[PDB]
Length: 393
Ligand code: HEM
Ligand SMILES: COc1ccc(C(=O)O)cc1OC
Image (cartoon, rainbow, N blue to C red):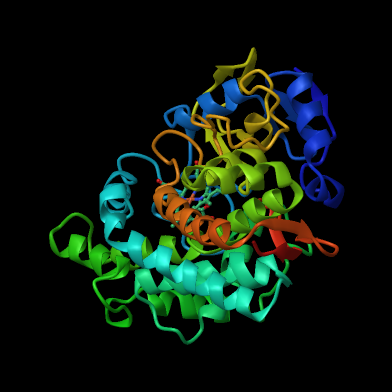
């Protein structure tokens, strides 16, 4: 069994993980990370299988490094993400309906128009702007919390909260050790927003509570289902949108493709999720000795799954380093796979579609105009700044 002291959460890896991915995949199906006493999987075949194999590889002992058999979680674990069947079943079914294609039909017009308003306002203002601040971050922060049905006061808390959540999956470091003085402030505010009386419209929050009335989940599950939406909903989409915008800005070939064929706007996002894999890593815990990739993972030990590495595995993907709108990216693992596969994927897709729709209409050319700054995070490839300059037709 290959053994290595490679550190996936060293700052150099986090800055640029591609060498690490290649080393990982090359070495074998399974690499023992001596530093963390976890078993790493980087190839598409094993990552895909580990993800779907909930029976052998559970989520309730944590999907971060921390082992909940022994270690105190930083917050009450997600009753979706950090739950196994049968406990997972009813909260999952509630969100899978509420966030599913048919349910979002009612929001498509509105999100597309909102994006048009945002893009037209921005371009009226300037042809030189930050793609992160002015687009990737602006847009989800309009439409998503609205659709959930939370108030406008405090929305600035969503990103630091999500950032903390993603950091928490990794080891203790000045990334993860981000607050304490403010973490409790953030947790106090998110939880408050989950209460039935905090929520408005017949938005997603109210629909969770209605499902509870029908007995699909309990009233004590309801706020925690809402909470899932407020932890996973905003930070993933901002950073995913920052990534697709970065990819276009540095791939003028693929921008020209989108312009030519408007329909690639609906599926550009998924190639960007494969290519970038915003969510890089998740852990599982072995429920028993499992023989995967020639290796036996001892019962009780953790696997670390490298979604990025799998999404760039040449065993599965032709020229995987290429950002290619002509790829069929179906079967990518950027949203995971199996029973825990991103229940929010349709929302993220619609957000991307709306924003790309509106931008491709108005923007001939797009270039990097300044240094880009990544925000380092243990789990989520995240973005501080992507300065761009556009040319209008
Ligand atoms: C509004 C947007 C989103 C929402 C509301 C959302 C919500 C969720 C939720 C609640 C889960 C847990 C489901 C379960 O355990 O059954 C999940 C899983 C996941 N999401 Fe998302 N998500 C969103 C966008 C994204 C994006 C853009 C990505 C990646 C770029 C992403 C990556 C994932 C991954 C990798 C998992 C799998 C967790 C696992 O296998 O343990 N999500 N999402
Ligand atoms: C994909 O990542 C997540 C999924 C669900 C949750 C959740 O709070 O349900 C949180 C996540 O990251 C912080």
